[PDB]
Amino acid sequence: RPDFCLEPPYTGPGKARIIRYFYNAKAGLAQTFVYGGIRAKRNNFKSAEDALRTCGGA
């Protein structure tokens, strides 16, 4: 599993409130979170399905 997939979501320093997805490795499912619009970390997807394709595990 890519290393970033286990990290908590990162809103970042931005003031925007965009709804993104992170892989919740303890649930084994994608979670929404609020993203501030700049300086994303890698556990940050535009869809549940992208989060699971990248982070869901072989």
Image (tube, grey):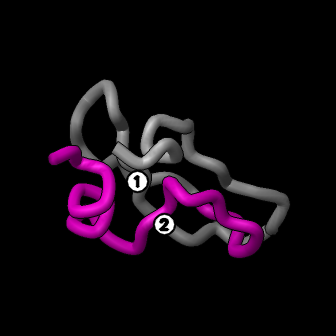
The residue sitting at 34% across, 33% down in the picture is 25
Q: Is residue 11 above or below residue 8?
A: below
Residue 53 inside the magenta-drawn segment: yes
Residue sitting nearer the eye, 1 or 12: 1
**Does residue 50 appear left or right of residue 15 in this picture?**
left
The residue at which mark 1 appears reads as 32
In the rendering, which numbered label is found on residue 5? none
Residue that numbered label 2 is attached to? 19
Circle 1: element type: strand
Say whether marks 2 and 1 touch (CB < 8 Å): yes
Q: Is residue 21 left or right of residue 13?
A: left
Whole-number angstrom distance, CA of label 2 to CA of label 1: 6 Å
Residues shaded magenta: 35-58
Q: Which secondary structure is most common in the magenta stretch?
A: loop
Q: Residues within 10 Å of mark 1 (few under 14, many from 20)?
A: some
What amino acid type should be assigned to the residue bearing mark 1?
Thr
